Length: 56
Length: 457
Image 1 (cartoon, each protein chain N blue to C red):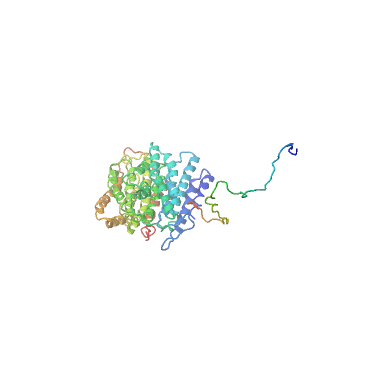
Image 2: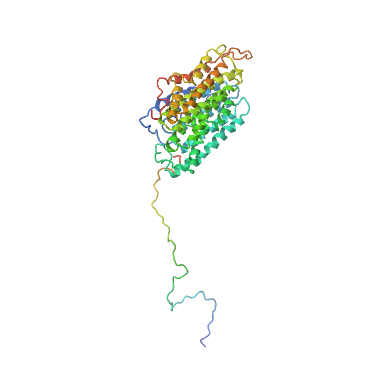
């Protein structure tokens, strides 16, 4: 019969897709990003005049 | 201009040869003291800042000149002592005075409260080493520990006081910036804010309570008598009471009311003990309590007339009490005991020093306008505007002001001296020079006392 086929060595992970079904990419479990990214500004500080301490 | 040449005194004493030392330390200090009067006296309507906030200008402080006046004088009377011991030990305890002079200039000049605090307690460290060593009698440690555990116990509450002000109301810094200060609302939470700023200056300026800090420092003598002049500088070193009461708490005077009453009884009871006492140095030690108690009264009234008498008395007492201690040292170097009754004999054995004894004693009383008449009388005049009752108590004190001076005179004006065989030479050329360098600057203040009292004068 044509039923006989030997594995020989290994599968080596085969990739095949045809049906897909709704694609499905993003679901996971999380609903929200939560507060998003924190506000951070970049401008590079010049010198900053006068120290905070009593002795200057 | 002021700091840097004072710091250069430190390598001066060490680099110079063993035969000299004392000649270089005294002569070079005198020319720096001349230059202090040359520049600091110039001021406009409101005294403008010197430079950046490290050492600033003087607004109502001619008291810096007094520190410069004692800058060589704290070396003249210490000549009799220290000479017996090692040459390295001599250099060490001249440099401890230089370090004292370094920190004492910084306190009066720098118009601050935050950095002023770390110069206020910084004067205590060199004086501690000075007191705990060279003391001829015992209980140096029963006076040395009491020197710190009275002052530091009261002054460490300034860390929780001063920092608390700058965290809420702008910053303390320049004092010329200090007009951000709003009047205190007067509440039970604001009680300990006022007390912490006061209790620090309640110790250095002696009252009736917590006053035992001063007599222990004077009776147990550090070195001869020249270091006792630095102990006079510590009393006037707590001058920040002029600055705190005016700026930090202007509305608060209701809580000052019990503290005036404490200092008012620190005038009769402090004078009464200063009568039957045995030690010659102690009878100056307790008269210095009452004389500086007059200043504390004047500050807490907050009237413009009282600050005139307050600033005058800081300079008045700074050159009269130090003058009296030099006379006490001149008897301590000859008789070798501080007893008043045993050391008895003026004019007969001490012919020219007795006239210096008279001039120093009478200055404690209200003489023709030298400085003490501009000092004491100005406070008494200002107390009547506070309350009418004051002069009934203050007048009794004016009777006992004679009883410090005349009792010190009479108990030495007896020409017996049967037990005493010493004191052959009356006074050395340096010893008579000490007495002149204290009274003659006050005699020059008779002509112009503008540079003796100046808070908006």
